[PDB]
Length: 79
Image (cartoon, rainbow, N blue to C red; front, top):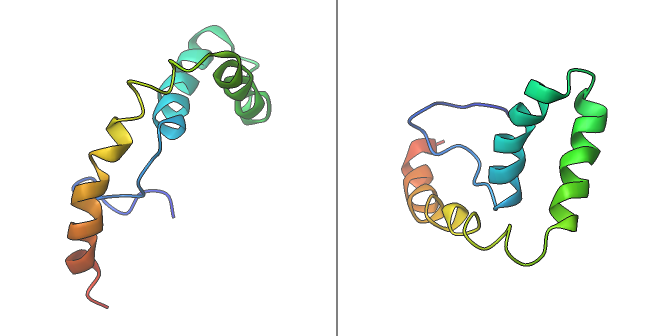
């Protein structure tokens, strides 16, 4: 939905989510008019512009929280 719990393994990201969720707040410090509308299509214009490097180091982060979520969420649900 948006935030089940801090200790619970929320939805797994995938590089892009790690970059956008971390770059969006940066765009706000310099772009006050950057509303969710332009903020959604702005961070994307940069990601596609980057070569095969922006998704090299920030892509392994989404592969570490998936080995604990796929195994921990099985018992966290129990419904």
